[PDB]
Amino acid sequence: QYSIQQSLGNASGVAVSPINADATLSTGVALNSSLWAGIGVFARGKP
Amino acid sequence: LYPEDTPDEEAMVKGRLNKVSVGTSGQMIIDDALTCCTQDNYLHFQHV
């Protein structure tokens, strides 16, 4: 086929604006994962 | 006759020139109709 332009100018050709979606925005956070961190002396490991 | 060259659409609209394009079925087609009117007072169209 042929390219579909966006934000058409002053005459002639037609255009399709880029897909607009904002009410669908959401944040993905686990909020249930639990992990622990610490320091210590171990026999084998990278210092 | 002049490949690798493209016209300026906005310049043609300002100069009141009707261009041609390629249709869906591969046939050359007139894609605009404008008259020799300088103003934009609904008179550059040929319909009225």
Image (tube, coloured by chain):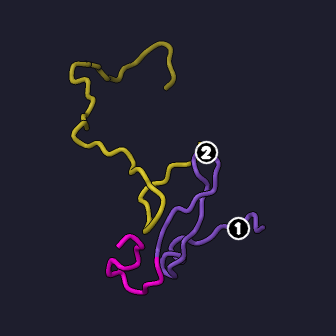
| Residue B28 placement: quadrant | bottom right
The residue type indicated by label 1 comes to Asp
| Residue A9 placement: quadrant | bottom left
Please identify, in this view, whether the residue under mark 1 or under mark 2 is nearer the observer. Answer: 2
Percent across and percent down for residue A13 are: 48, 58
* Residue at 54% over, 76% down: B17
Front position in the image: A34 or B24: B24
Q: Is residue B39 magenta?
A: yes
Other-residue count near label 1 (Cα within 10 Å), few / some / many at <14 / 14–19 / ≥20: few
Q: Main secondary structure of the magenta part?
A: loop
Which residue is identified by label 1? B5
Chain under disc 2: B
The residue type indicated by label 2 comes to Ser
Which span is picked out in magenta?
A: B35-48
* Residue at 61% over, 45% down: B25
* Residue at 57% over, 46% down: B24
In the image, A21: left or right of B34? left
**How much space separates mark 1 and mark 2, taking CA atoms?**
23 Å
Chain rendered yellow: A
Chain under disc 1: B
